[PDB]
Image (tube, rainbow, N blue to C red; front, side, top):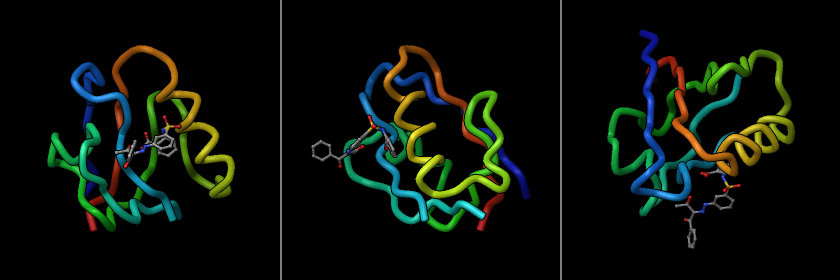
Length: 82
Ligand SMILES: CC(=O)/C(=N\Nc1cccc(S(=O)(=O)Nc2ccccc2C(=O)O)c1)C(=O)c1ccccc1
């Protein structure tokens, strides 16, 4: 089950996720992801905007998320539900 979740990123500064395939390791208080509710811990992160996460190292995925969260605009996260 694959779901795409688009977040406006206007009411919250950060996603509020940790990443540990790349999985959502945790969802944190105060982030856009927790407020939205559609993504859950354990979901597998497949794509963020136009960046596919296949074969990506954890360090590179953190760098990608940092760069995307730092730029203004919506963020679309495609996950496979746990
Ligand atoms: C809720 C939340 O998000 C949190 N800290 N967030 C966060 C932390 C570091 C870098 C980025 S980041 O701007 O570089 N963006 C990311 C880069 C990599 C992976 C994930 C993110 C992300 O946004 O989740 C976002 C917190 O609990 C928090 C607690 C106290 C004070 C401030 C924040």
